[PDB]
Image 1 (cartoon, one colour):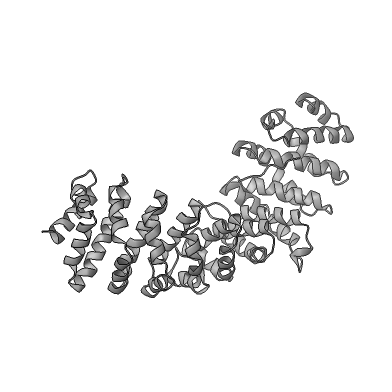
Image 2 (cartoon, each protein chain N blue to C red; image 1 turned 180 degrees about the vertical axis):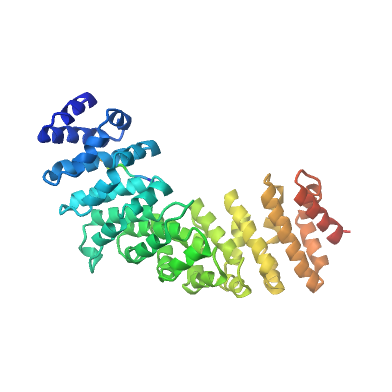
Length: 7
Length: 423
């Protein structure tokens, strides 16, 4: 569904 | 690492640079992989401030930091995405698509993909706010290769979310608008871009025949077949799903998949070491042997019947279930001489062995294919030779036992074979 952007 | 309290005191300074530093701090908290404190940020009331920072054209950094922070809140549960939509974020993110700074418009693309990715409602809400025009405008270059790689992959992924989900499917005019770009991305040479483009096509082909036709008419089946033969599993998986979706349609929509050469790849797919590939490939096969007799003939000519016999003999149970459906469809629509051919490929004994499975539905489909095969033998007069074959490989004990078990549709069809073919 979704993507968190990381460091 | 700042506390949420200090972020709050910083965001409430009415000092733009203090707010910028506090928004960085929030952004870094929300970008940590192990429990990001999304609910704490939401519960502190920070979302309306973040949304207001999206409109600060003068301070592009705080635009980027807020879009970043909001992106990760929208990446959470449906409630946390709701909190972002409830703060007015959709119109603000759509304005940011026009940002002269590439990293900021990219961040808006990403955030809108997270919102649309929540489900049908937010996806259609993103569309009603007019996101499709500025998104497509970002891909309006003569050659996609002049776009930055990560930039292009975020566009592709967000567009695929706009194609995603049913109940309801995306609006018809929205998909007509997206498809031309989507086919371009389907011919791009980046694997990540190809994979998400294939996923979008698989979503669009997951519905009634009218939706299938709309994709087939854009001419993507030859490209889907080529991606079917790729070495990258993340590409094959959505490509096979889209092909499998297309063969659920009409017989002539299925014919376009056969004409593109898809069957030549299936020896590989039906022996693939990845369970899901085998299942989806067998499921696709089941919907092709549900077609016309000349379409069953192409399955035979491509040498796929022994591969169906092998997947029936040894595979994960879900794959064996799809194989049984393939044979029942084959036996339902095939000529008697395709049926004869199926028996000479060794179908009987793997088919008898699956009669001891503890699943009531696979049993039902297998009896129904045994019936179909007998009726073919009945037009040749070989019902005696067949009943011997079924008895000789241990299949008659199975039917006798099935003749008396729970389900009603089985034993009414189980006794039918006993008192019509064994006496």
